[PDB]
Picture 1: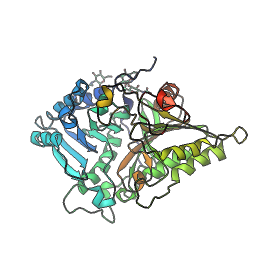
Picture 2 (picture 1 turned 180 degrees about the horizontal axis):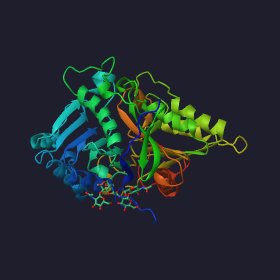
Picture 3 (picture 1 turned 90 degrees about the vertical axis):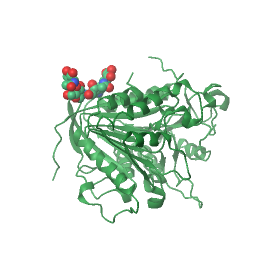
Picture 4 (picture 1 turned 90 degrees about the horizontal axis):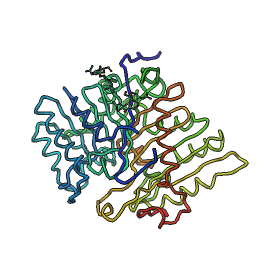
Length: 416
Ligand SMILES: *[C@@H]1O[C@H](CO)[C@@H](O[C@@H]2O[C@H](CO)[C@@H](O)[C@H](O)[C@H]2NC(C)=O)[C@H](O)[C@H]1NC(C)=O
Ligand SMILES: *[C@@H]1O[C@H](CO)[C@@H](O[C@@H]2O[C@H](CO)[C@@H](O)[C@H](O)[C@H]2NC(C)=O)[C@H](O)[C@H]1NC(C)=O
């Protein structure tokens, strides 16, 4: 019936990037600190699933002092293969030709690197970001292999420490990326047993998490990349939504009930109707915190206003939407593709979901993504820490109702 429990002493830590100048009145380790500490303690293996690499000023054609943390991350990674650590890096194939200075330097250092052509395989991209260290620890979250991800962009991830069972489960997902990064690869009709898992929505892994029992599993996207035991990302996410009885707090960079960039536009109401059902059938309080910046897709506005219109005193329907805007001063505004909140996570009164994907259809049907799902009885824990980060952001001055003036938010914002 139920698969074997895990005996490892797992400890989870939420790790954040807080961009320079973003202040919150009255603390977690930073992505940069957590990463440097994962590298310093690596003795055998490092697997990185990645979207792109821009860790240096040279990569972005800037001269920013705040790129130093990214350049120190690259320097540490270059010491790993020479000292005997097996480094494997899966990266998304860019759509055109692009310079690959970081990956060259790591190849030169002895790391193995495979480009994955998800466009050929699924019409999507390899979007996931995660690290697996020594088959024991992993990072899963929103931060890219990008110096801007350490200092100029707001990020949210988790580091699971001392949790070899779950790290090995994550390595299985990595191994599918690693296989597909080979010449002549196609998606097998059936994935071999080597990739399958017992740990999923129906039977999550029983773990001991910061000293108390928890239920954890890893979900994966797109469906072609899921062996039969592997819960698909979208199914995991909708299960948290459908099980919520008091609130759903969602902080995601983009939300769009469409299959974004489809030449014939394609409506995609899967998550939308989940949130509508939750609030109308079960009286769930839904708070959606969507990021906004100069690159936001302007069609988001009408769909977000559609959701917000459901608030009704007498139906106990209570959806609220805010936009989170990272301010950019003059010098910051010259950094390409920065000053935005990249977080992607969901928390309810009983469950956590930490993902790598934005909430539009292609991320769940074509593009590679992963998410960690944890449930755990008892006040406190990982779940209350994530709720606290959400409420911090929701109540901060960086969060704005949809009627807010564009000239109040401290940055370009296409949704206002
Ligand atoms: C993960 O496991 C390591 C190794 O067991 C823990 O590190 C040790 O913690 C003990 C007791 O807390 C210390 O006395 C040692 O100095 C640590 N290093 C060793 C034993 O090599 C670590 O605390 C656990 N948690 C995390 C987040 O790393
Ligand atoms: C689970 O254990 C981890 C590891 O001890 C906790 O993370 C530490 O939290 C303190 C503050 O409480 C930080 O100053 C440390 O830097 C963190 N350690 C590491 C290795 O990052 C985490 O808070 C614990 N979570 C719960 C819910 O108890």
